[PDB]
Amino acid sequence: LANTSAHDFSYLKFVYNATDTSLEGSYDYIVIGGGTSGCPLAATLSEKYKVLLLERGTIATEYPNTLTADGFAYNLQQQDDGKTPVERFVSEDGIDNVRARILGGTTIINAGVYARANISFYSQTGIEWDLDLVNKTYEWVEDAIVVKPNNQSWQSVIGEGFLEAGILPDNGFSLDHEAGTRLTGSTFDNNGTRHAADELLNKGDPNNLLVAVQASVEKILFSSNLSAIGVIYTDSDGNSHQAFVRGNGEVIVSAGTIGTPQLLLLSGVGPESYLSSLNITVVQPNPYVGQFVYDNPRNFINILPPNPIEASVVTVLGIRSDYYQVSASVLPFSTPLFSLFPTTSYPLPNSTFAHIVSQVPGPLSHGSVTLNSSSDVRIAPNIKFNYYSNSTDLANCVSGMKKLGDLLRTKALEPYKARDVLGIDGFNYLGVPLPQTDDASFETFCLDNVASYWHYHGGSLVGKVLDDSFRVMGIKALRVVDASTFPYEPNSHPQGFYLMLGRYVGLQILQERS
Ligand SMILES: Cc1cc2nc3c(=O)[nH]c(=O)nc-3n(C[C@H](O)[C@H](O)[C@H](O)COP(=O)(O)OP(=O)(O)OC[C@H]3O[C@@H](n4cnc5c(N)ncnc54)[C@H](O)[C@@H]3O)c2cc1C
Ligand SMILES: *[C@@H]1O[C@H](CO)[C@@H](O[C@@H]2O[C@H](CO)[C@@H](O)[C@H](O)[C@H]2NC(C)=O)[C@H](O)[C@H]1NC(C)=O
Ligand SMILES: CC1(C)OCc2cc([C@@H](O)C#N)ccc2O1
Ligand SMILES: *[C@@H]1O[C@H](CO)[C@@H](O)[C@H](O)[C@H]1NC(C)=O
Ligand SMILES: *[C@@H]1O[C@H](CO)[C@@H](O)[C@H](O)[C@H]1NC(C)=O
Ligand SMILES: *[C@@H]1O[C@H](CO)[C@@H](O)[C@H](O)[C@H]1NC(C)=O
Ligand SMILES: *[C@@H]1O[C@H](CO)[C@@H](O)[C@H](O)[C@H]1NC(C)=O
Ligand SMILES: *[C@@H]1O[C@H](CO)[C@@H](O)[C@H](O)[C@H]1NC(C)=O
Image 1 (cartoon, rainbow, N blue to C red):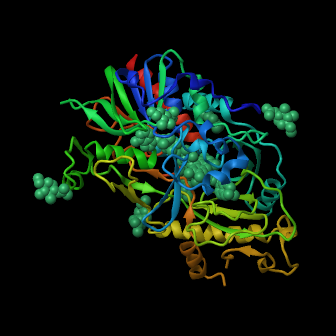
Image 2: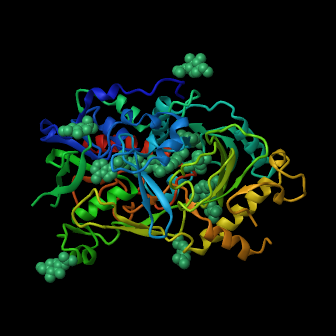
Image 3: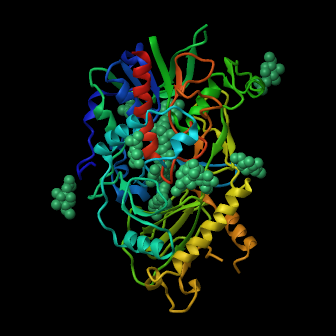
């Protein structure tokens, strides 16, 4: 595990403005998106080969509130001016949401919770994983940016609550996604310093890795044995640039659940009838590009203790197969955190509150990413998740809400009631309280008060768009590595999986080429 230490910006020595035309040329690999998967992928490929990493955002030093736990709220409260690290969107379902626009991707703006994948996930996928190498690669990530959290009073209250509510067993401190209650890792260190995927660029070879920032990749270029041969990208001034791969080298899209399918569709990889309807020339028909896009529901209550509670980062997890639960203790604010609640029309907290949360696994409900512009990658795509379209998801939310009621009735949580009465009506709530306990009362609560967990995934799935080598089927020299790749969450908190996956696939590419 990592130690408490400053955020390591050594890598800025090989970070350049995309306005620099001397970056245009031929590389062994081009990685699109300097994010959770892309940064460890590019660093790994750079051990042997010449790599260009292209990121649309700027460097995290421009937005210092991205570098502390205390700055998390600021990034979500900040107005989206096109340049900020948080890009705001609303799904077609009407649920507010965010994605990252910054070198380091979503590991620069996220809640810092670190977990390994459920060890059963690898067999569930039917991919031939090198499991020894998966674990070596988890340790490579953890040694860089993961700490054992110190005790925080509220996380300890919630952990005692989860155990008293029957979320057993007590796993103590563990990075593994296992049934029961545990202290997990964090990418915040014990001084509140954020550590993130950009720091994994410090593991790259500085003679072989180049990083362009404010590089908006608009199009994947193809041969005229269809192969990806390069990219077009625009700089902050609006000027265009090209970069190519050479010989046995490859383009990898790491632009996230939203950005990957967007760029594939803009580049003519996707459903023939849809792309022909936009007069986008089809290079490779695949009816699944932008399909099977998922967002795990977040359902929640907010309690307002009569005495102040200490603000905390999330470190204590209550895991069952059918729901994943945490709680944050949150300082009050008068400017909303965009997407913390599902719409801007949510009450503001006047005092410290506990946000007590359950996540639906999978989920089984899915939707799609479609283009909003047939030409401009800077124009956000349309995204729809179809929350609770699958009844199994709704049943799982009912089970999770019953368990949050159990948590609120524990001796652990009793001291946080406003009134010493028998029920959970003894708490004071911000927003809608929990349930009458008939299925319809819990289903109404689940459906009406859903928010994003921010763990959306899918849109370029293995088994639909990709093979088990993460290659785009029917195309040479093109791969996809990021959260677009799997339909079900690997665990409650997937950044650890996707950090591992960038390096893992980098190591597979290097091996396939030897
Ligand atoms: C608010 C929030 C809180 C979260 N908290 C947690 C948590 O505590 N723990 C956890 O495990 N997970 C958490 N997650 C989820 C997790 O961080 C993400 O699922 C994961 O980081 C996604 O990784 P990715 O590589 O797919 O995408 P990203 O990290 O978003 O990387 C994609 C990158 O591509 C860039 N890009 C996109 N399009 C282009 C383009 N055309 N050209 C160039 N660059 C482009 C983007 O700017 C970005 O930097 C959180 C998510 C959010 C949004
Ligand atoms: C870890 O992943 C495994 C495999 O996906 C899960 O096991 C499955 O769980 C469902 C229960 O909802 C069962 O119907 C399947 O039979 C299980 N598969 C196997 C291989 O046993 C497991 O639930 C996940 N664990 C947690 C804690 O999330
Ligand atoms: C504002 C506040 C309390 O802070 C951080 C936070 C983290 C999580 C986490 O599980 C994820 N992802 C859920 C909710 C949440 O809300
Ligand atoms: C962590 O903060 C403490 C103060 O509580 C200090 O003693 C220690 O040197 C700090 N380490 C850092 C900032 O790296
Ligand atoms: C890149 O250069 C342009 C001016 O050419 C400037 O406006 C922009 O801020 C620079 N971007 C970064 C990320 O340095
Ligand atoms: C990998 O690590 C997990 C714990 O994260 C462990 O349970 C598993 O046995 C390890 N697998 C291999 C192949 O060593
Ligand atoms: C596609 O181009 C044809 C002309 O070739 C035109 O008739 C049609 O309306 C166009 N469709 C779109 C959506 O641009
Ligand atoms: C729910 O999801 C599963 C597929 O994972 C499927 O068997 C079932 O048909 C789905 N229900 C609906 C309404 O789609």
